[PDB]
Image (cartoon, rainbow over all chains, first blue to last red; front, side):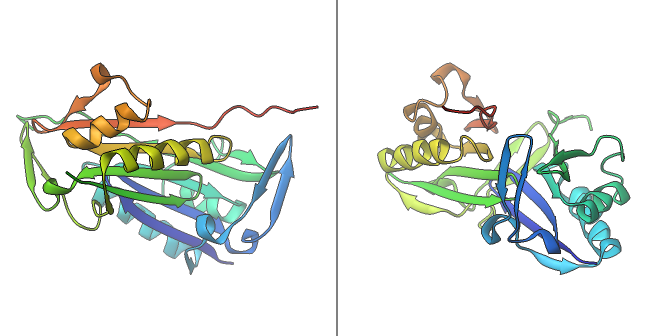
Length: 115
Length: 115
């Protein structure tokens, strides 16, 4: 019952990527989409759901004002974490390869000088 | 005359970040904000603009059917790299703290079959 969490800051942008641990390595095909669940893209720290949702909430609060935040989530467990973090609703979860998927941005606002 | 190129792929996302080398470790103030051009976020392979443009071109073609490519460039030389790669028009370049800045999201091509 493990999800892999990968957080990497590159320039302006922080990517928070989650993959159900058991999906790693697998090849998915569904509706004309071929997807290899590769180590370089999908690896991360294996944690429990509750623990990933905590860390994901924490990363967003820390970053959302300075950096673009991209959330990518692949897998049923990974997408429930994004839901439990309050980042999406169960009905805005999509699919990819016949597996739940979410791909979201938190884009930054112009800054408020009197703010 | 050198630009830092930092490329990292995670989840559905490849970030290509470019920064003028002489900007690394500086602080930029704009409308009450403080941008720290910090080593963890900005710290790439140091290269000559023409070589950076070539690598940027190649990574964009590499991921065109597979990932979203997010580009962030900070500095005069870095933005000129984005222009010289054919990725942005000179007039599209923004600025951030009196320093040129561009952010771009290049989503993958819609899927197609070949006979």
